[PDB]
Figure 1 (tube, chains in turn yellow, cyan):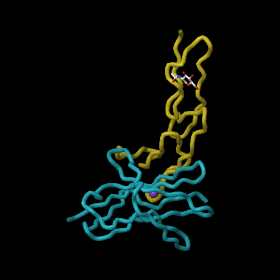
Figure 2 (spheres, rainbow over the protein chains, first blue to last red):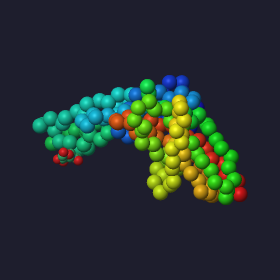
Figure 3 (cartoon, each protein chain N blue to C red):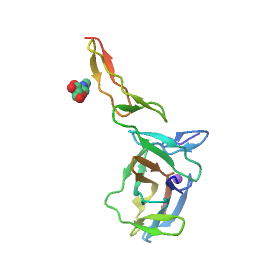
Length: 77
Length: 102
Ligand SMILES: *[C@@H]1O[C@H](CO)[C@@H](O)[C@H](O)[C@H]1NC(C)=O
Ligand code: NA
């Protein structure tokens, strides 16, 4: 089992990435995790993916804006 | 060449309060030397070490970024991570645990 400050990447316990970053390289027992910046207009979706921030259409209002970790939230007016 | 920090998972050091100490982040880099910073874990949060004395010691095939304890104090007990910034990349080391005796 991994410690709470770590994250399971393969069957390997690794340091996590900071909020705006996805895992670009897995750690080993002896080496670091590599993280890359998710670019503006994207959010960290899994450990490894930047997903494009969805746009709330004209027939909707934005409840919460797109952060680096979570998608936009939309509801009807 | 990937930038790598060679701190082994569950790495630890036993050190004496009042003695000086040098905590090493061994860095592999091939071109421009990255910006590296130390931080100390409280739970699952790495508080950056901003006011602290740090230095580089360069060797043929690896380089050491050192966190200086001048001297070690009982409150220095705990877990430390080291981080490197290269362009848009962020390389995150395993935590190394300091055990202090006094
Ligand atoms: C989202 O940001 C835009 C500006 O880019 C702003 O007009 C809008 O009110 C924001 N919505 C929320 C819920 O923060
Ligand atoms: Na490491």
